[PDB]
Amino acid sequence: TRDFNGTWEMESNENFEGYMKALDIDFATRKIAVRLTFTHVIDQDGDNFKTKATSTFLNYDVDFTVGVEFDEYTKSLDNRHVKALVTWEGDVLVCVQKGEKENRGWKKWIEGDKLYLELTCGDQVCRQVFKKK
Ligand SMILES: *C/C=C/c1ccc2c(c1)C(C)(C)c1cc(N(CC)CC)ccc1-2
Image (tube, rainbow, N blue to C red; front, top):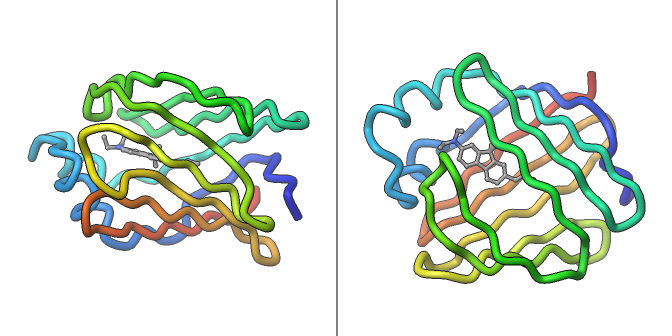
């Protein structure tokens, strides 16, 4: 499926710390973030994505149109300017964030009832799994 719609509840989160250190997330935010359960809400209509990630203390919202490059400010993450582009590779949703950090981006894909997220920055890879709620 290429349909990522739904409310997704975190089930596994491997090496979030190394990914966040690659981004120069400060020690403080890192320790809080590594313990929190995240809910990821995706409202997808054609190419148009409205996405949310909510926790009891840290939140991240981004909207994008597949295939349309956009300048992004990674507000309350590492607060950097990147040139973002989200495209399809088969049924994998792939984002490249061009900027100062190397190999920065993410990939989303679904297997069965699970959403998989791979976050990359530098030589670090974080893998998260969500169960559809
Ligand atoms: C499709 C979503 C991809 C994606 C890329 C980067 C991040 C995330 C999802 C989050 C919301 C899981 C997330 C959280 C953080 N935190 C550390 C500052 C917690 C707010 C950083 C980057 C990403």
